[PDB]
Length: 204
Figure 1 (tube, rainbow, N blue to C red):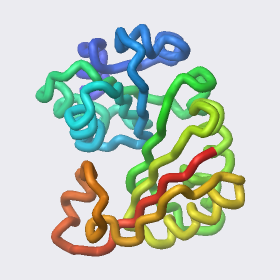
Figure 2 (figure 1 turned 45 degrees about the vertical axis):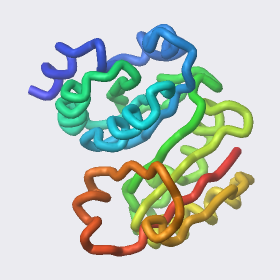
Figure 3 (figure 1 turned 30 degrees about the vertical axis):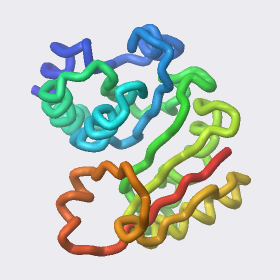
Figure 4 (figure 1 turned 90 degrees about the horizontal axis):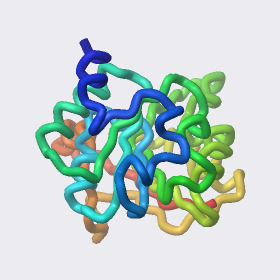
């Protein structure tokens, strides 16, 4: 009963856009910046980020209620106020956020959709970029990390062709002096493998 667990926990989980869009600051109860992760899996990333950064409000977003319920288990345990989980029903994120309502966007290990005919499904494809540009402020940024070389190669070109500026590029994240990295479950699971992790900060 994924849907059941989510519904019993409205202090953390948002289920319908009507009670979200333009209302996120009211929902958190302060004007702290709102940073969103799209495709938040089982919540290790948003949880670890909320802990590192008490004065930032995080929203973990997933299309699947099942996996969001696992994120909830993690979020309930931590018990900190600067997180919320959002179930999205398939619509554009503009149904859930007003233009400029969020401050930064995170994409972690997003589905690569390697087949050419599935380009449109990649979260770094231009129609998703249109949506992200709207919901972020002017000069708003996407911070994107993945171990998928093909996806990262594609996304650098997609970002650039769209007209975004690349502010930083990491081609071996774990080997760099980058600090504050919070690993996803996937990232943990495979840390022992030691394959390079790619990262970029891109700006609209």
